[PDB]
Image (cartoon, rainbow over all chains, first blue to last red):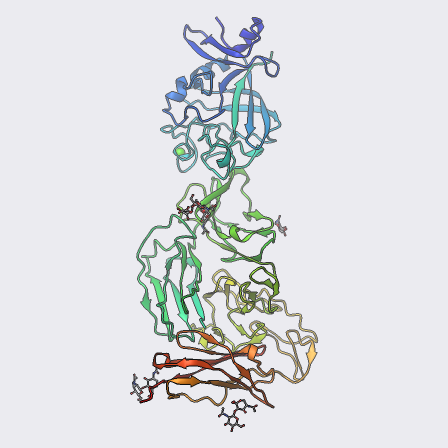
Length: 216
Length: 423
Ligand SMILES: *[C@@H]1O[C@H](CO)[C@@H](O[C@@H]2O[C@H](CO)[C@@H](O[C@@H]3O[C@H](CO)[C@@H](O[C@H]4O[C@H](CO)[C@@H](O)[C@H](O)[C@H]4NC(C)=O)[C@H](O)[C@H]3NC(C)=O)[C@H](O)[C@H]2NC(C)=O)[C@H](O)[C@H]1NC(C)=O
Ligand SMILES: *[C@@H]1O[C@H](CO)[C@@H](O[C@@H]2O[C@H](CO)[C@@H](O)[C@H](O)[C@H]2NC(C)=O)[C@H](O)[C@H]1NC(C)=O
Ligand SMILES: *[C@@H]1O[C@H](CO)[C@@H](O[C@@H]2O[C@H](CO)[C@@H](O)[C@H](O)[C@H]2NC(C)=O)[C@H](O)[C@H]1NC(C)=O
Ligand SMILES: [Ca+2]
């Protein structure tokens, strides 16, 4: 039935909530969370980071099919996000909330990944937003790395270094998948949820919502 | 009461041998001299036993030499104690790969409570990686690969004392020992103020000398003495009063001196450098030649002493005429004594035109107690300070030292007392 959240929205389903979608050109279904009551309305949360919840340091394959319930935080699964993107043309909006008591987003004009035999290389273009003037996600998208997914450029392994899977450069200005640190421990931490250009290298965000749409 | 002087044979370790030397000049320290890794400062340091053999070029000092090619686990933070009557005294430093990737542009940095400071790092062997700063062995922050400064700074406006330590710098991927070190030293009070609550003024010091915010005196730079450090020692000397000759032929062209923490580690007056291999451009002169000769009537600026005014005039800059000041001399003092257990009144009589005062005159017991005069005399020439000691008994025998320190220099002369017992 429903491929992505836009199709849910246009189907008048305008209500923030969990929905079941189906892979394009296939008969496989992957559940997720749609953010209708939001911006334009109709976003497909590919990830959230609201509290401790379930970790992220997981098998490369786990970051492949996804993990975590969509009720709270989760990752959905690169493969779905990989195909679901080359179908049409999607953007990407990254929104995060800090402890002190602020919040900002970042909007990419176009986003998509690649073949598993290409390590799901990310590609982001046309950057806008309030959380930076420079793409916090390492330009020239690198391969997605994991505990056992050394496909980065550090002469070392950023994943085992920064905890969790992410498009690490030689350990870039970002990693939204890194040890959820509490209120009074949200500073001078390396393996923490950081988006650099909006806070600091030592900051560990309190919230982290990554979501996508096409151009409805 | 305790003149310790740690020596760092070039903090930048290479294929060549390096060493540490903790010299105690003046006092025959009782509590044994220590040397070793200052584990607290640079944390996560590897715990290796470093042999501390004795040195025989100077009267009382232990050394630590890391033999060529063997110099592998030498990076980090070392120090060395002294200990006088129950109290302490330590001097800290660092040892780092000469190679590495960055370079401190200075080993130490002294500031007063509330100075905006810039802990820098010269980028040298640029790699396709990220930058990371590490205080004490703890992570602070990093710099993203594509925008890594040229002179990697670290800004801390209004530095407090608990904000000092050892800031490091390494390209993300690399040993916690391939890092580059540098110490920042903040003192409890602000410039020129010392005190149990910083409500007293420091004995203003010249020739780049720092002031101990615990006592009020200055820790002169290796090359000058005097209550204000205005006195230019013998060319190529060092030591609380100068009685220590820099060894190596070219003056001190390779010694990085370190004094008690309120000061730090600077080259000896006359050399610029990180290894102090460089003499000084004309016009400047102090330690690390941070001193600019503002010699008035255009006099010779000596890269060690300063201005060499014409006869008839003296002054840091020759800005004053007057009878030339002559340092003190502890005159007329026996080498032995032989006294009987009882009321005892030692006396130090000392010369010098800037003439000492009981403020400036002491007598130091062997164990290290400082003793002040009970009554002061005075005369045409020479100051007579009489000390009084309750009941001096046999165990006090040893080597006492009359010590005078005015604004024209410091001087110590020992004598051997031998309290016997009356039948
Ligand atoms: C380099 O910089 C790091 C910080 O970046 C310093 O390390 C931290 O230092 C702080 C300040 O002292 C220290 O905080 C102390 O934490 C302990 C326990 O968490 C508390 O307990 C102390 O008293 C109890 C008795 O009730 C003892 O049982 C503990 O052993 C004792 N703490 C210790 C181990 O010394 C202290 O009360 C608390 N201080 C206060 C009052 O705030 C952190 O524990 C240190 N953490 C780290 C990362 O090591 C480091 O000291 C510094 N190095 C230097 C000296 O420059
Ligand atoms: C300082 O006090 C000392 C000790 O109380 C005095 O020194 C003695 O002076 C007499 C002369 O009055 C000499 O004969 C002795 O030889 C001195 N004692 C010693 C050290 O041997 C002296 O009165 C005082 N000095 C001055 C000049 O005021
Ligand atoms: C302090 O001086 C006395 C002077 O008598 C020293 O005593 C002895 O001096 C003779 C002189 O030739 C030596 O042969 C001995 O070695 C000394 N005997 C002792 C007690 O060791 C005494 O040694 C001196 N002490 C110091 C620290 O110099
Ligand atoms: Ca790698």
